[PDB]
Image: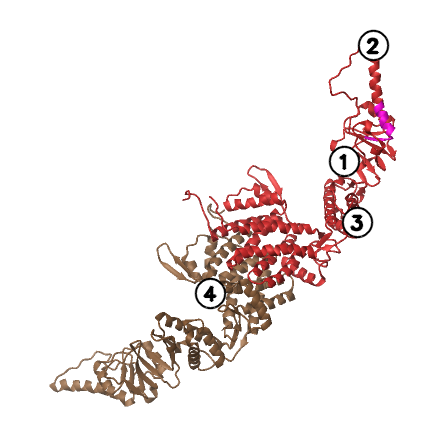
Chain colours: A brown, B red
Amino acid sequence: VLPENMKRYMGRDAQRMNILAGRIIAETVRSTLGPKGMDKMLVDDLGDVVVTNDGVTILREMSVEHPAAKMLIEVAKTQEKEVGDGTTTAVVVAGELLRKAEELLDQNVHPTIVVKGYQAAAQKAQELLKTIACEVGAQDKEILTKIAMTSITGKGAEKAKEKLAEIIVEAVSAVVDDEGKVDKDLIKIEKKSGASIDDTELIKGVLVDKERVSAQMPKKVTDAKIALLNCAIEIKETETDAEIRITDPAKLMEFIEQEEKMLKDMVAEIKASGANVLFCQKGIDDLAQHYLAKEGIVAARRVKKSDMEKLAKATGANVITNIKDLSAQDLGDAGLVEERKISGDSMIFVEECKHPKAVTMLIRGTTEHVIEEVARAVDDAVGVVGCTIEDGRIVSGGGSTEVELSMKLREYAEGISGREQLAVRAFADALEVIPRTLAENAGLDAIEILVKVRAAHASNGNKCAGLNVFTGAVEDMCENGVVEPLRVKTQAIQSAAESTEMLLRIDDVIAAE
Amino acid sequence: VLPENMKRYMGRDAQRMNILAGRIIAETVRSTLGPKGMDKMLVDDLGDVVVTNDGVTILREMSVEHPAAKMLIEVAKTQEKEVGDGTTTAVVVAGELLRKAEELLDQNVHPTIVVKGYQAAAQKAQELLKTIACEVGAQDKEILTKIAMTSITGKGAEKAKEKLAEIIVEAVSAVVDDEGKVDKDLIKIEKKSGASIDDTELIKGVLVDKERVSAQMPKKVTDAKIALLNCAIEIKETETDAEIRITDPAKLMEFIEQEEKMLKDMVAEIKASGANVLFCQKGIDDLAQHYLAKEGIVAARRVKKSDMEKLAKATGANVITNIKDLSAQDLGDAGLVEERKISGDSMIFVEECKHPKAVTMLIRGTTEHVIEEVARAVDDAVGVVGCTIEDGRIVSGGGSTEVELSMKLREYAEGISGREQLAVRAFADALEVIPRTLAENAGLDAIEILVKVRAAHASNGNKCAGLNVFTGAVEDMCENGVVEPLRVKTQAIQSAAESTEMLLRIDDVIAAE
């Protein structure tokens, strides 16, 4: 029936082969999983080198032969399209989940039961997460400082964790407005090597990496009135083609003086507004700079269009098209506009804004690489503070959730009884991989840590436990402000289970040669 | 350095390959392990068929290619030479033990620790077995009947388990003499299809499958005096070559009458002893049968030399070489010697012996195959009764030992602490394979049974639990007389651990191509 050369596996042979292939891949990528996960270096037959942690990338680049291994590759791609993250997690968890599930099959527990038990326990797991979650004041000063400081600790920047935690909480709180949605676009990160980390600071305003275009401009302006124009301050010309037809010598002068008046009127109007700072999107003719300078007006030219819009938002200036439309109500306020040297380079500071909706955090450090990591550290601190502001729920980490779930699910298992309890029992036992690889990747005794932690948790409670990989001992997770959003864990479970259910649904595998 | 063609694996690659090969073999044979283990049919390239359960045989016959698989074959052979049994057990247990041990290696627990923890827990396991063992009266009538009856139940012969349990306990108790060593050689098993199992019985004597050689012999003898001779009752001749040299006609008669007297004197002497039964090892001339018959003496000829010795032991007759040495003190006693037809065939019954040291259990049944299985059933009942008579210790089965050990070892683990506790913890977790495969091979829910049993055991106690595969529910193991010798379990652990220690000691594998 089939072309000679085609190969086929069926029943328990199809199952054995498929599972085994998937498992081996899982063992290959699992070494990247987690905060303490490491990376791989893949050098193709051409010499190109890729160093990554991404499961898809590793699997996409490698050259697989086995059909069963090629079919699993599709799983990794669908995981990326659907959810984005959890590629490595889903493969590793899916493998163990399938392995433990097959142990039930060998016991003669119908796969419809195993899959149902997992579904049921998985849905109940989300409820338990919502139940054990510790509710907090979204804008609580003290707890916020713990989130911030907890992130900063264990990094080069820890030397000034107190000041940094302060500025970070304040920056988010300012731009968030209501309680709350945050747009991290209103918090700029400028990093310039020089000084130390102690010099880092928050600026309730903006730090632009530009200079005052002309030398003759004032070096200091107080109570500045900033103007934001996007139209070029040049001699406008009609869209329709035009040309002057001179017929008398009197006109040679007539037109020259006409263009001079137009140019002077332009500049004169800007001054008439009371503006002492002007940001133009297009060009500024040299002569215009000269008059601007003589009027003690500070000007900037050739500003990016996207920057013109960021400048409007930050400074609170209204972009006007026609000068005719400009009014005092369109002017923005800055408490201070000053030229400062930072690591020698000249930069402009717009600081002491009344109630800025965009702030900048100028980072200092003894090295480029240092300020880069400090920037990453803050990107996270803003992130986690944002998570708590939108979802006033927090939860202990160090695999505390999975332990709570394992306990309660075991009791629930007993309530249900029958074969279905075995399926719910296996789900609870499967959850232990998290604790297992947390301490394994950390280089802690996985067996001993789990025994000590679980015991300590059962005694001291929920907010007096977890694993502290840094000190290698139980602690107070709450006191140490070591918390993550519930959404992290909830979404992880959801996407993870939906992938496992797809695999569990397959009862027939037909792979061509 | 090495000849091109040679292949080498080292470090974690040598370890991965070796473990994996061993594991796959273990999965192949594990389906035979246990009371509910099944058999395999192996048909070589020649057509020969072997159906066995033996691990060595299966592995010896199969044609392996992989060097690592060939090296494991040596394990199976050494297991046979050293201990005999536990070939399949040792391979299967050794595989899982190695797998669980490698999980510790990945956690960075020095293999010297893992091996030590197993050794320590294994030695402690033997102590715990001696501690939990329930001591009983070696010759307790009632408990003995439970051992007997428990064996018989669930077999074709169960219809008469009460009578059979009675005869079996009595047979062993009689031949054991002191308390106690038993020689199963004193309990003969004769099986002849015909009648039913209800007709089975014990005979305090012997049942020989022979006939009375001559028709004219008495058909019934009371208070019989049995003689056991090994010398032939013929005309003796000198070792040195001799010949009669007749020189007178008077001698032709002289010698004839001389040989007649010698022959008559022989026979006359036997009668003179008061013997009415005679067992001769060699031949009996027809004329001798005639006189023996006329004297109402029963005789048997051409008896096996080994049978002559069994006849001496059983009947309590003393084998004499020269008739001159025979005396009344050499005579044996039998309460009855009678010819009976059993399934038509004629057999001799030596029954109603005073205090027989050898008994026979005549088995009846509607089929040959039935009486054969009944014989096996008794061979076991005698065995287990023998185990209890020599070691007045018994213990609950159904994996009760391993559960007790798992509990106590876990506490001991906590006492020791450190990494060593993880090794002792893994040993305790490894013990669960027994419960796992007991219910798996039985077709019971392995997970659910274990949960129910352990809980029930923790509540009802030690003698109110175990698994009862027959009813598929907890029971009272003691009330049901479902016990095994401690020696079974103790030796199993000892031999098993010594094989595992050999594997654990290997840190270098060098296999040629």
Q: CA distance from mark 3 to mark 4?
A: 68 Å
Q: Is residue A90 left or right of residue B490?
A: left
The numbered disc on residue B310 is: 1
Q: Is residue A99 visible?
A: yes
Number of marks in picture = 4
Instruction: Indicate which disc residue B249 carries.
Output: 2
Q: Label 2 sits on what residue type?
A: Pro
* Subunit ID for the residue under disc 1: B
Q: Which one is closest to the eye, mark 4 or mark 1? A: 1
Q: Is residue B79 above or below residue A254?
A: above
As helix, strand or loop, the secondary structure at mark 1 comes to helix
Residue labelled with disc 3: B162
The magenta stretch is B265-278
**Residue A211 percent coordinates (x, y):** 28, 79
Residue shown at the point (85%, 22%) measured from the top left: B264
Residue B267 falls inside the magenta stretch: yes
N-terminal of the pair, mark 3 or mark 2, is: 3
State the separation of the CA atoms marked 2 and 4: 123 Å
In magenta segment, residue B47? no
Q: Going by the image, does A194 lie left or right of B133?
A: left
Q: Secondary structure at mark 3?
A: helix
Name which residue type carries label 1. Answer: Lys
* Residue receiving disc 4: A36
Q: Are marks 3 and 2 on the same chain?
A: yes
Question: What is the CA distance from the residue labelled 4 to the residue labelled 1?
Answer: 78 Å
